[PDB]
């Protein structure tokens, strides 16, 4: 709004070209805040996806060795589950906050689809973790002796 129309003060002055340059710089500064988790969401999903992959392995009993490697993930899921839930509330707000002061839609239908996808795997991971934890506890009690 602030650029305004050509103002005449003895010699006509045009800010038309200048206004476009300001818009370019303004969008770049706005883009950094909006794209803050744009890169981060993919990295968190890339990192988050690996945890689900370990869960997909599963398997009860069989070799003791595998248990030592798989057992660490449960210890990681507990800490990540507690800390991740606390970290989840601000992340939800960040996607919502940009939507309010950004008329344009980021990644179109994909960004909303991405949130629904994360929620379905997070719930699946929690149920898998509970079953894994009961099995882990019996084998770990033997491991503990």
Image (tube, rainbow, N blue to C red):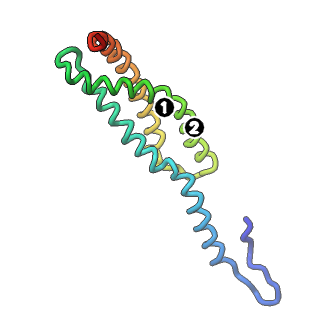
Q: Where is 46 relative to 66, above or below? A: below
Q: What residue sits right under mark 1 in the picture?
A: 84
Q: Secondary structure at mark 1?
A: helix
Residue that sits furthest to the right in the current view: 10
Which image quadrant: the C terminus?
top left
Which quadrant would residue 1 be assigned to in this image?
bottom right
x and y percent of residue 83 in the render?
50, 30
Q: Where is 60 relative to 38, above or below? A: above
Give left or right: position of 65 versus 20: left
Give left or right: position of 27 versus 57: right
**Callout 2: few (<14), some (14-19), or many (20+) C-alpha neighbours within 10 Å?**
few
Distance from disc 1 to disc 2, alpha carbons, whole Å, reads 11 Å
x and y percent of residue 49 in the render?
35, 36
| Residue occupying image coordinates x 70% and y 81% | 14
In the image, 36 versus 11, the foreground residue is 36
Residue 16's label in the rendered image is none
Residue that sits furthest to the bottom in the current view: 11
In the image, 142 versus 30, the foreground residue is 142
Residue that sits furthest to the left in the current view: 63
Which quadrant would residue 10 be assigned to in this image?
bottom right
x and y percent of residue 24 in the render?
58, 68
Q: What residue sits right under mark 2 in the picture?
A: 90
**Callout 1: few (<14), some (14-19), or many (20+) C-alpha neighbours within 10 Å?**
few
Give left or right: position of 115 versus 65: right
In the image, 66 versus 39, the foreground residue is 66
């Amino acid at each position: 709004r602030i650029k305004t129309p050509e103002d005449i003060s003895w010699l006509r002055i045009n800010l038309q070209p200048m206004k476009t340059a300001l818009d370019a710089r303004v969008t770049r500064w706005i883009r950094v805040y909006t794209d803050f988790l744009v890169n981060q969401f993919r990295t968190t999903q890339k990192n988050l996806l690996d945890f689900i992959e370990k869960t997909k392995d599963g398997i009860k009993k069989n070799p003791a060795d595998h248990e030592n490697l798989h057992d660490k993930k449960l210890l990681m899921s507990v800490m990540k589950v507690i800390s991740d839930v606390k970290d989840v509330e601000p992340r939800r707000e960040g996607i919502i906050t940009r939507m309010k002061e950004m008329v344009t839609k980021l990644k179109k239908h994909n960004v909303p689809i991405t949130e629904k996808g994360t929620d379905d795997p997070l719930q699946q991971i929690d149920n898998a973790n509970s079953n894994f934890i009961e099995i882990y506890g019996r084998v770990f009690k033997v491991k503990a002796d």
